[PDB]
Image (cartoon, rainbow, N blue to C red):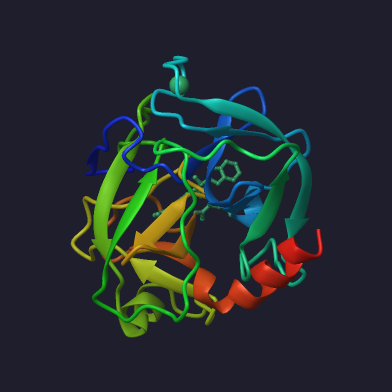
Length: 223
Ligand SMILES: *[C@](=O)([C]([C][C][C][N]C([N])=[N])[N]C(=O)[C]1[C][C]([O])[C]N1C([C])=O)C1=NC2=C([C]=[C][C]=[C]2)S1
Ligand SMILES: [Ca+2]
């Protein structure tokens, strides 16, 4: 997260870190046994880390649970990142508490202009590299589909939306993928991609979760 601020220990209880010997992507807890992340974050041997703040220090509120299965969206396209979403099941149910909580799925898609909270342990510099150990936060509005497609002509599908500021300086970045975009108490986006980080006229692109609620509910119910 570039241009954001330190969230505060466990102020984002649904935020999870996907670990394969090191943090490689973020994710969102949707219930005690399931996590939502980006399809491009898929890999074998994933360990979900909940209740984290400083990912390099065991502070006392974390729960490390191995994934038992991963399900990449049936229409995921690794080249264009269309349908960039995946489900990860925990080998054992997480113990839900105030610092480890699930985030609700959308009932309807959010409108442009709606303010959202984007979070992650990604790079904090737009022209360099500096990874934070504590969770970073960023308030960002959903941009019109017009400004989104204008910035990325021919690259935006109906399964993506842009959020951020066209002026640049504030945005998600590498290390944030798979992470949450929460608006009005619901998971509306998943950190997906973008042109560089926090660059003017190049806002962050996020998977549009509202288009997948049906798939998520049916998939988790059958697995
Ligand atoms: C993700 O943390 C980043 C998030 C980038 C957010 N960008 C924005 N908000 N301006 N995404 C990657 O860097 C993606 C994935 C690839 O398809 C290409 N790239 C683009 C164009 O954004 C990460 N994803 C990966 C990382 C490391 C290795 C593989 C995927 S970090
Ligand atoms: Ca920790």
